[PDB]
Every structure is written in structure tokens, then in C-alpha cells.
Amino acid sequence: MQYKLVINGKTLKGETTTKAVDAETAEKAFKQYANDNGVDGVWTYDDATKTFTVTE
Image 1 (cartoon, rainbow, N blue to C red):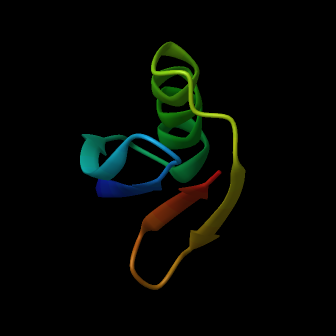
Image 2 (image 1 turned 135 degrees about the vertical axis):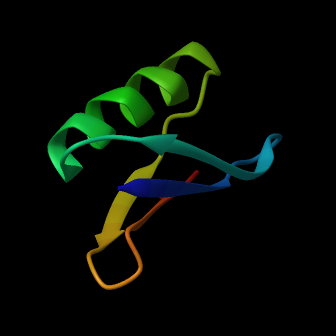
């Protein structure tokens, strides 16, 4: 499944995507991505749209 990450950061804002077999695998990839880019926010996940959102 294609999962989407919506980033609402202080300085970095946009969207990116990743492909994974399940949501937990996608979450790990996105949490690594956020750490690599210096984003430290709160997360939500909406199973209906397969979208994660992170806000600083």
C-alpha cells in the first residue's frame, strides 16, 4: 500500500510518500525520515486515507 506523510513543520512543510506492506512498517520509515530531517512533532494516523500527519 502507498502511505502518505503530510509534514506541517516550523520550517519544513509539504508531503512525501512511502510504500509498505503494513502501517507499522510505514511508521518506522516515516519516523526515521522525520528524525533525519530534524522534525520533532506530534503524530496522527488516519486509516481511511492511509495518511500520517506530523505537526511541530
